[PDB]
Image (cartoon, rainbow over all chains, first blue to last red; front, side, top):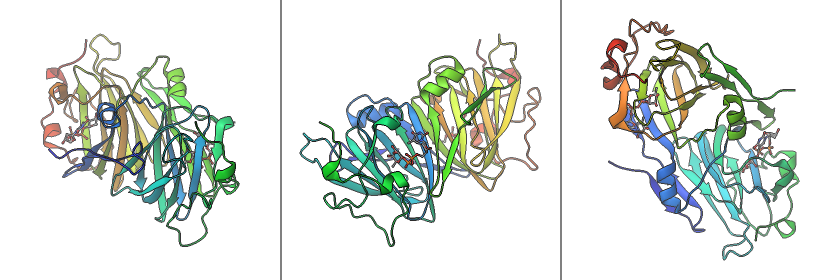
Length: 184
Length: 184
Ligand SMILES: Cc1cn([C@H]2C[C@H](O)[C@@H](COP(=O)(O)OP(=O)(O)O[C@H]3O[C@@H](C)C(=O)[C@@H](O)[C@H]3O)O2)c(=O)[nH]c1=O
Ligand SMILES: Cc1cn([C@H]2C[C@H](O)[C@@H](COP(=O)(O)OP(=O)(O)O[C@H]3O[C@@H](C)C(=O)[C@@H](O)[C@H]3O)O2)c(=O)[nH]c1=O
């Protein structure tokens, strides 16, 4: 009896989870998600309808993404390698509007971040490759997808990069925070 | 055009899924699960409440597992390495009671097996290591867990294994199919 750990971040609706891992002669086992435990920690019901999996090379940066309608809460983790994962509060009425939190998530540390609807999300790959898995509370709606550019000068996100990031065209063309659609 | 594929196996309630993978110069993206797409293929609504993650060395065999109350449907895949994954029908009244189907699931082939409640499940690891992920329709209930021994001589599972498998103590002590608690 050790157990799952949940820790609210500086933007308290963002939660850092750490599973309890059971090792034995075969390798290991852990629960990567448990609805009862998760809901207890969050303080409200959450339902996931899609799971996504990406593989990215060192220096790849994906984000900052959100859906302005059909907004998605995201529970994210790394199953290979290491990333720095960032959540940006885009709720206009929030006292932390325009602030961000970031944590290193890796296959080894098994940490996860819960990033509710109303946030933008992104990550950068620190390892040779990283595989990133996340669960979403609503479906992909490309018509509603929005992007804020990684290096926005108002957000001032400290990405641990040693070189220019490798971006998709969509992400390279992200809007400035000042011009971005935000949530109430 | 390409999209997710679903194929019913010889025991038709067991479904083999293969996601559509989008490659680009960052790596790839795929939806590992989509509730709409899944429910359409299966023909009935589903709710998953727990996700499990295990890591196992070559020759590790886990199974054959089921819960006789709080029975779990399982949607399983490999995110590292390769396994041979087996589903055994333990519904006494089923036309396929005592039959099994098996498929190789790997990180590279991205194949998944949907194994309904009423089945036993196991896998053997073919690669140096494998990481095996699965979603379950009900919670872990150790009081209700049962195991049938991997090499039961009535099931006659053709495990593509050269040498003796590495088993947990529990799995070494699995019951004979002839003596096992089964579902109606
Ligand atoms: C996001 C997504 C993409 N796709 C397809 C569209 C395209 O062909 C390919 C790649 O899409 P993208 O370039 O938009 O994928 P990507 O840049 O990996 O987008 C993701 O980034 C992380 C950080 C998030 O927060 C996610 O919500 C999502 O925005 O996958 C889906 O089929 N379903 C999905 O849910
Ligand atoms: C199955 C399970 C185990 N545990 C703990 C108990 C124990 O300390 C550790 C390892 O348990 P086991 O040895 O029973 O794990 P394992 O032998 O990997 O069991 C699994 O095998 C595959 C084939 C399946 O079908 C799964 O549903 C499950 O039965 O993990 C959980 O916390 N939650 C769970 O859901």
